[PDB]
Amino acid sequence: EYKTVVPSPYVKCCGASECSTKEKPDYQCKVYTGVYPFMWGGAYCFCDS
Amino acid sequence: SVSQHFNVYKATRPYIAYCADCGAGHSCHSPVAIEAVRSEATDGMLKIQFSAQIGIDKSDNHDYTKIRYADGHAIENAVRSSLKVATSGDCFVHGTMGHFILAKCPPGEFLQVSIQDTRNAVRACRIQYHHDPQPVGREKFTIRPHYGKEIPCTTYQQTTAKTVEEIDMHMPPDTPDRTLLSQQSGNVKITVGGKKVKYNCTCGTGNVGTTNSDMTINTCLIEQCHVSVTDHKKWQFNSPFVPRADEPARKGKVHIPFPLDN
Amino acid sequence: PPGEFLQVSIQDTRNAVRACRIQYHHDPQPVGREKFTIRPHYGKEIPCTTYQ
Amino acid sequence: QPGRFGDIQSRTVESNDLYANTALKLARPSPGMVHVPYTQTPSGFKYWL
Ligand SMILES: *[C@@H]1O[C@H](CO)[C@@H](O[C@@H]2O[C@H](CO)[C@@H](O)[C@H](O)[C@H]2NC(C)=O)[C@H](O)[C@H]1NC(C)=O
Ligand SMILES: *[C@@H]1O[C@H](CO)[C@@H](O[C@@H]2O[C@H](CO)[C@@H](O)[C@H](O)[C@H]2NC(C)=O)[C@H](O)[C@H]1NC(C)=O
Image (cartoon, rainbow over all chains, first blue to last red; front, side, top):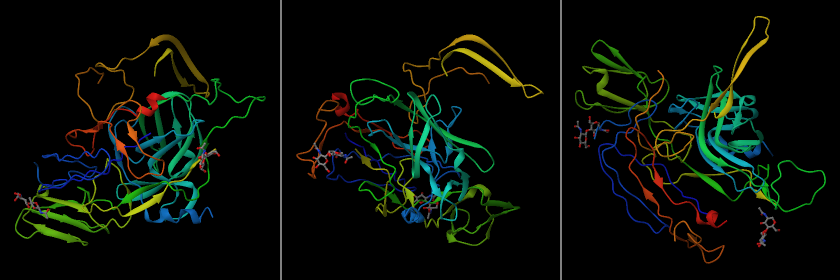
């Protein structure tokens, strides 16, 4: 049996990021733009889009 | 010793995560969020992982009748006699240790775990899990007989010693709080409360930085600033439901109890 | 949850149990094209009627 | 092949290489949330079992 390992998501506010390929079984990474995360205390960062 | 086995959990704290349905079909942030359910035992001993820790009190000390959990920014305690696991019927708890709960439950479609709060409130989460254990062998019995055969059949042991398998931990992120802001006519005032805070305000110039004392900023509206706690000396479990801090580097590893045996 | 009968009970002044039970074939069917049991954390939104 | 016997492979139990083909596809998060979704065909070992 296999187990899919998925780490915590990296969110960056007022900026951008790109991810590099790695030698790892079935590595699948993508960068999603224009997000507004929410937590229990309130909004996470200033930049709206 | 049993008390010596709890050295590792001295540098960890619980957390609150988003779990979809928390009792009445309404999404709600909860400290009893479920992450994974493991069923590699042949006899059907479920292994449940959740945010709150068993066996540790708020003052970071071994104790077998208290459950500690995160609420707000602090850590509270709850009685261990108020722990329930149910899958279409109440089911039995065989042993609990830290993050993990061991239970055997009747066939059902959904799984629920609940604890009681300091204010006698009920906190629970429910996920979907198709549970149907086929007993080992060639007969689908339900209850052990008083005259039968002995056949190999694996299970989880209750030993708390170090095992090869482990999970990983990482530094918690900055948690926004909107309640540390107050309005004073034409000023905003931030209350430290004993925890270092970080701010960013676009009113005026040069209003960014991190402080750990009460201050006031003039000519600013309440909506024009954002603050978040920063200290976070403890550790957190790497969860997909909580954002990861700036450093992408694994920081620590923690063993997980209850290995597999014949 | 699904079942064949329904029961409502309250407690008397004398701490007795007063209950009355009828038959009612209850078997809910979620809206859409899938028969799920617990709401998911990633999905679509279908219009749906409820009691306020 | 994904979903059938042999989704993940290894030369020996102690080997450090792994060939995996399980069709791991990521998806965009729901707005106002912090979660990473993914769709992946179930283990073919259980299907064979
Ligand atoms: C504090 O918040 C301001 C926005 O209110 C951030 O300023 C943005 O900076 C990025 C690049 O650094 C620019 O692309 C944006 O146009 C800026 N926004 C505005 C409104 O000017 C600033 O970066 C934040 N600083 C910190 C330390 O978080
Ligand atoms: C329970 O016992 C069985 C048999 O004694 C174990 O299976 C063997 O485990 C050893 C490792 O100690 C391997 O070297 C052998 O190759 C295994 N047998 C076979 C036929 O492959 C089994 O691992 C034990 N259960 C657990 C959880 O350790």
